[PDB]
Image 1 (cartoon, rainbow, N blue to C red):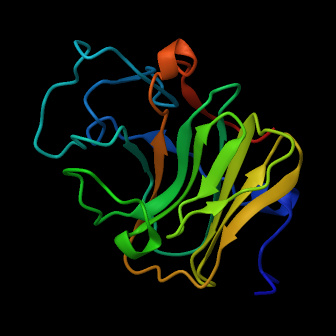
Image 2: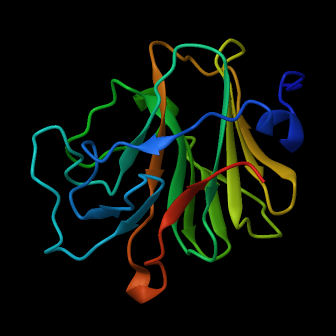
Length: 195
């Protein structure tokens, strides 16, 4: 897998799209900024209006826009957080119950599990050998070639590519700010403009 189509960071950043969080999808304890660029996990009693279309088990929120083609990029500040999920998914994913976030189930994501523990959510999962922890992560989808690539924006380096993906139908960004990790991981994710 030669990844001839996969750009370096600068080339990926050229394809930046404006992403906003879809609060109607969100797991109901997620809290959003007014501009819908930031999300964090609130307390149990901090509840969005319950609706039947929300994630109910997994601490997830989807992004807009969804798309059927092209090369699309966006960037997220993860800072010093100890856990998070980033990537893209099919718009048709199931939202209810314990989810398995795999390509077969329509997800292409990287997960920070804890400090110094990052995986691509292949099955089985692939440990990512990160030496300089990212404070900002870039996501680049090339629909036509069937690839989704992840970048350490801080180190200006590629992290991981899922190649030969079977993208069918619309894709969209997906995010999780992770669990609260005893207070270690309460900060938000923040979608940012390219630097």
